[PDB]
Length: 233
Length: 233
Length: 6
Length: 6
Ligand SMILES: [Ca+2]
Ligand SMILES: [Ca+2]
Ligand SMILES: [Ca+2]
Ligand SMILES: [Ca+2]
Ligand SMILES: [Cl-]
Ligand SMILES: [Cl-]
Ligand SMILES: [Mg+2]
Ligand SMILES: [Mg+2]
Ligand code: NA
Ligand code: NA
Ligand code: NA
Ligand code: NA
Ligand code: NA
Ligand code: NA
Image (cartoon, rainbow over all chains, first blue to last red; front, top):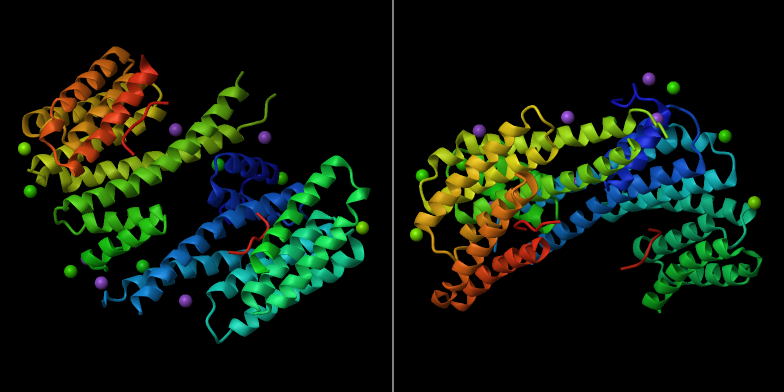
């Protein structure tokens, strides 16, 4: 790895600088290097890893959607293979980023994560990046990719419900994304709606236990659940 | 070049797709490939080349400014070499992009550009990318880099005043950027103000010759001259 | 477009 | 911050 010669602490420091400069590809490479040092990640370091790759894959997903739309229109004047070729190029890049993240989780973040907050975080991430693979998958391994996302989300859910209070932001963000998995990927809008509503209601009833700062963290994610329920119902 | 096997027309088509997907690094690579086919560029193709590299270097400049600010603050607790190292990394990348553009202009866009609209466009671009080099240059070749920008802008100005009407958008954009060169790079704010005011006034007096669409093109750039004069006076 | 964690 | 051609 090109980051093998840099100190772990220097990689984390530069990841934070890259975030300030909105250089997310750099940020991701720095955090990949930090992960490959082999030590577990702190809470803040996990969120640096997540922010970096979410922004990288977010740009790829947005570009893929633009190109896929153009391609679908083209298939309703013939302009040659270029639209498909370039959509395939972006798609392959996107799949490579997803494979990279999943590789870091499998070697060896998840197996060393024993605390609920780390294990749920990583399993949610595993579900997320299989979901992004599912967004562009067509047919053959599409079913297996979808089941891999489902399995990761489900293990994360089981742990979060046993070990975390209903207002825990990690638990809430997991439920949010799993509900979108149901709605957008698994063709299960009723499951999506039920999960979002139950998650929201159980969090509501637990808010009274929280400090002002924790209340703000939890209600921010609860608003995203409500925003989806407004779109879906 | 990695684009040597792709058709010129396919490169231009994919550059347009990349712009729609806001994939400007891809867009720049496609247009570099198109330039290296060796044929002159049409007006639309020149603007694809410009849009691509302006967005790429624009992101690098924004990141460099963020990091340079952090570095300058650090030099007013000691945190090691990381800020400088990462600023240097971004700076080197930026310089590489500028060198790439200048290389395309020198081999061989400028020497084959005979029409005023192409020659002024390319010479303005040469001034622009030497200016971006000057923004990060310190001392030794800083003076020579600044003079290279000045020389390119000046040749472009001489042609534009001989061959173009005062409302020509290329002429106006050249004057705008050369005035910013004077203000920001050459420590010549009075020259910057004089150029912007004379450019604006001579364009004003020529607007009556224009169609509605041309009037809109010219007044848009004239507003940028006025915005600068408002900042500067 | 559904909202996921940002 | 001065404006250049966008
Ligand atoms: Ca060490
Ligand atoms: Ca452990
Ligand atoms: Ca050909
Ligand atoms: Ca010629
Ligand atoms: Cl391609
Ligand atoms: Cl670095
Ligand atoms: Mg607990
Ligand atoms: Mg003329
Ligand atoms: Na090493
Ligand atoms: Na074609
Ligand atoms: Na594919
Ligand atoms: Na070739
Ligand atoms: Na340090
Ligand atoms: Na340097």
